[PDB]
Amino acid sequence: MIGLVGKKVGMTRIFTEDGVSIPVTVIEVEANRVTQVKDLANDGYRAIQVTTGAKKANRVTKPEAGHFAKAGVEAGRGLWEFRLAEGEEFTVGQSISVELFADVKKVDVTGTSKGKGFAGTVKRWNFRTQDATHGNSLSHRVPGSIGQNQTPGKVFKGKKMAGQMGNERVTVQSLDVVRVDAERNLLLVKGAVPGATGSDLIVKPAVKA
Amino acid sequence: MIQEQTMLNVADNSGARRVMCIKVLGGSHRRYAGVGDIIKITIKEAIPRGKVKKGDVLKAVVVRTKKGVRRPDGSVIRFDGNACVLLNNNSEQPIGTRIFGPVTRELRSEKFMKIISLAPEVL
Amino acid sequence: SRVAKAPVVVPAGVDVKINGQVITIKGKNGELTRTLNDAVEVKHADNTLTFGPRDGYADGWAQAGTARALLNSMVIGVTEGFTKKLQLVGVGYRAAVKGNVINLSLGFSHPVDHQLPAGITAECPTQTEIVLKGADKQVIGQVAADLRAYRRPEPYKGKGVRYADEVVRTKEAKKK
Amino acid sequence: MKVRASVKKLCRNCKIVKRDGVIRVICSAEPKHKQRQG
RNA sequence: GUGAAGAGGGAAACAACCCAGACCGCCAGCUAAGGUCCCAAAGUCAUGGUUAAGUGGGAAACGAUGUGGGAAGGCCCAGACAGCCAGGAUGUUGGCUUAGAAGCAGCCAUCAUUUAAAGAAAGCGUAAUAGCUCACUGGUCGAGUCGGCCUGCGCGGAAGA
RNA sequence: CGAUGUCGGCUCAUCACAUCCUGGGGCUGAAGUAGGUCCCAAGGGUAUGGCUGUUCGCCAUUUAAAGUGGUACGCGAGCUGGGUUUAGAACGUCGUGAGACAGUUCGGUCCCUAUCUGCCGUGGGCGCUGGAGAACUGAGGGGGGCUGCUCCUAGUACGAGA
RNA sequence: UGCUGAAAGCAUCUAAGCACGAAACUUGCCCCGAGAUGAGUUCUCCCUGACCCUUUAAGGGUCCUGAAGGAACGUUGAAGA
Ligand SMILES: [Mg+2]
Ligand SMILES: [Mg+2]
Ligand SMILES: [Mg+2]
Ligand SMILES: [Mg+2]
Ligand SMILES: [Mg+2]
Ligand SMILES: [Mg+2]
Ligand SMILES: [Mg+2]
Ligand SMILES: [Mg+2]
Ligand SMILES: [Mg+2]
Ligand SMILES: [Mg+2]
Ligand SMILES: [Mg+2]
Ligand SMILES: [Mg+2]
Ligand SMILES: [Mg+2]
Ligand SMILES: [Mg+2]
Ligand SMILES: [Mg+2]
Ligand SMILES: [Mg+2]
Ligand SMILES: [Mg+2]
Ligand SMILES: [Mg+2]
Ligand SMILES: [Mg+2]
Ligand SMILES: [Mg+2]
Ligand SMILES: [Mg+2]
Ligand SMILES: [Mg+2]
Ligand SMILES: [Mg+2]
Ligand SMILES: [Mg+2]
Ligand SMILES: [Zn+2]
């Protein structure tokens, strides 16, 4: 089944009739507008491309605008594809709303995780610190050994080292769908999803059970 | 949130007064026990003519902690100290015959029903 | 070879058909088709099939005997057909057929349902007896072994699914 | 299954058989007699 | 003997092994060891065989109906080998022992009868019997079958960062 | 020998498989539960403490388990500096003595701003054949891969019973 | 672990044929990913003047042109050395 594109609003909670507090991420899902249908004959695969949102004219380049004009829809903040299943079919300029999830029990949510900048091995890879005292010299959060000796005489690819952490694509799987409401452009899912308030989210029905 | 070396008061008439946790049971590298969890203890002080003695090695269930317990609406119940109830090493059933101070409904197990019945108060 | 050199009489009622190595044998009790190994040359004259090796193949005679043996029981198949009987031993062990599915109660939580392949049909004359019938001797054997395997006879009370014929030796437990 | 370098018939119901390049002893009488060269 | 104090070709690389001793020049020719399907110069050469393991391209005692060659031998149309039918008996539960010991815990003996043949019993079985089966023999089948010898090539035995 | 820093720990690891646990299977002198032994299997997982410089080991208590080995007995231009080769001092022992011990004892300086390889991240350039903006396909690469207990089945199969 | 089955009248999981079989393998899940120079595909956007010279060729230069886009500057960010 296709998914949809949305915006992370923030977290809050739903209280239930019998005392449970459900923590929910609030996801804003406005109509997704279909901007190109891809098929086997023309593209080698089946998919819809969608936009959502709105975009500043003066910020819409001409290439971008011709592509939107072709589909018969107004500009949106970006473009995303969702693969089609056999029997799945859509048409250019079609609107897809959040009611798509009305009876989907769980969804996977993809976002761009918050950025933590250049991170040391303690935070990035949960390395353990060496001694704070007992004579340790200048080596508390530093990484330790990064290899063996003459054999192999090199450091291995993949070695866990410090570097950029976050600001990457992350998918969190099988979150409960707590509420769908198209009149308010809302989807509530149970739990935390990746990203900062404001940033784009891809929501798809869960690939697992 | 009890670990090795932690000291606990004792919420029964077993005669123990102060016990130390020498193992958090229930899994490899398991760090903490909380309300409802079983620990291994050594007895550091006991009264003169009770059911157990200083230096005895046994089990106990934790029934009050400072870290507390979370309830499903987000609430917290915290206690001013850590206490446990002594348990037979093998049967893991209570040594004492009376229970002191409040306990929590997290104990409602087949196993700890006797502790909640005896407790003055149940939170 | 002693087996290969022994002709297969094809009786009145059976229709043999050959197209290179692809043999087909039709009778009143179904039709089987087999592709004989290249190294085998088969001939069909009178009311008989005869077999022989083929110039250039190092193992022609061994192959021809297999081919012979097989075609012989293809003919038994579409005439008399084959019958494999099993029986259940153990309390609560029972079986029944509905259509082409054999329902096996064998001391498991879920009962067991075994789909019969094309050509094989089953009947229980008894809650504890399975009669398979078929024209393909390999398939009927494969099935009988599939069923037996849900609960192979065990050595302490002989309990399980067994071939009706089968000999199950039991043994005593380890003394205390 | 006994697995060893030297496999033999241990009784008259033992049979030596080669299966897939591997010498084996199969017995119809005594399961302990069953061997694989290895 | 070679290196040392020796280049050149071969042994992937590799002083010391194989071939061979560089005065200089050549965009001629023959050979040595070693090679000739492509990397890579020269046989996808000819002829007769072997191997089926990628053996070749690591490793022993020992194990095995792998397969090729050779010389002998035993049994067999007076019916062999395999399979299938049937028999496998009497003294007698041999003597001793033992609670029991009957072919089959153990010890000693192992004769004789009726036999087509059938051990005072080859293995399972029973508390001891019973019961299963082998040796052996008649029948059926109908032409081969058995396993030692000299030898070629293979197979397992064969686990390391 | 115009210097290749030694034991142990800490940090970080990587490989083998002669497999500790989990998985599959043959035999069992395997009734069940639980074991023994061998075969297949390297995917992941594989304890904290008391004593001692210890590695190891004994001990306490856990765990499904607390694996065996290679990696300069992995890892000091990464840390420690308790053991152990300096200079102080003492005891026992040896020596007439200076002194000695591979006996013990108290004390006792651990440098290096990374050029190249390598590795973790992140940019600039050019290319992809006029140039440009997006959305993709998915060759290839990496990550992940653990497991306890309880309940139902069922107090059933099995068992004289437990 | 088996089915059918000769070689070897029988037997035999195997020689031909056939059914199963594990946390290993290939997929399935997540991330990177066309510098995948074998540099791929789809949609959209932009550019429509002359001249001279030599060794005349995918030649060199001049005048006029200067798009789409990119970047620059500025206000900046749960993005960042
Ligand atoms: Mg995108
Ligand atoms: Mg940030
Ligand atoms: Mg630490
Ligand atoms: Mg310092
Ligand atoms: Mg410091
Ligand atoms: Mg170093
Ligand atoms: Mg190297
Ligand atoms: Mg196999
Ligand atoms: Mg010299
Ligand atoms: Mg050379
Ligand atoms: Mg000369
Ligand atoms: Mg050539
Ligand atoms: Mg090799
Ligand atoms: Mg005969
Ligand atoms: Mg030097
Ligand atoms: Mg192994
Ligand atoms: Mg052994
Ligand atoms: Mg491992
Ligand atoms: Mg254990
Ligand atoms: Mg070392
Ligand atoms: Mg240093
Ligand atoms: Mg010393
Ligand atoms: Mg592909
Ligand atoms: Mg990309
Ligand atoms: Zn045997």
Image: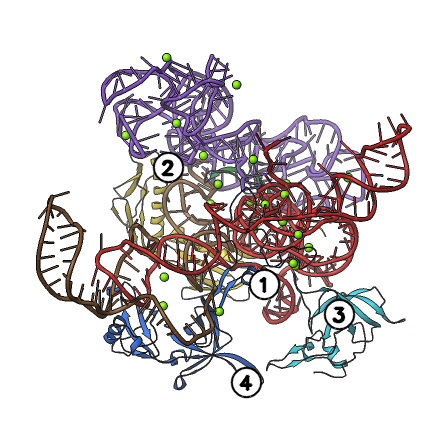
Chain colours: A blue, B cyan, C yellow, D green, E purple, F red, G brown
The chain letter for the residue carrying disc 1 is C
Dot 1: what SS?
Answer: loop
Q: Mark 2: few, some, or many residues within 10 Å (few <14, many ≥20)?
A: some
The residue labelled by disc 2 is C62
Residue type marked 3: Ala
Q: In the picture shown, does residue C164 fall above or below F37? A: below
Residue type marked 2: Ala
Residue D8 visible (yes or no): no
For the residues labelled 4 and 3, the Cα–Cα distance comes to: 36 Å
Residue type marked 4: Thr
Q: Mark 1: few, some, or many residues within 10 Å (few <14, many ≥20)?
A: few
For the residues labelled 1 and 3, the Cα–Cα distance comes to: 46 Å
Q: In the picture shown, does residue E119 fall above or below B103? A: above
The residue labelled by disc 1 is C91
The chain letter for the residue carrying disc 2 is C
Q: Say the numbered circle drawn on residue B86.
A: none
Q: In the picture shown, does residue G68 fall above or below D23? A: below
Q: Residue B114, position in %: x, y?
A: 75, 77
Kindly report which numbered mark, 1 or 4, lies closer to the viewer in this rendering.
Answer: 4
Q: Mark 4: few, some, or many residues within 10 Å (few <14, many ≥20)?
A: few
For the residues labelled 3 and 2, the Cα–Cα distance comes to: 76 Å
State yes or no: Cβ of the residue under disc 1 lies below 8 Å from any atom of ligand 25.
no
Disc 1 or 2, which lies upstream in sequence?
2
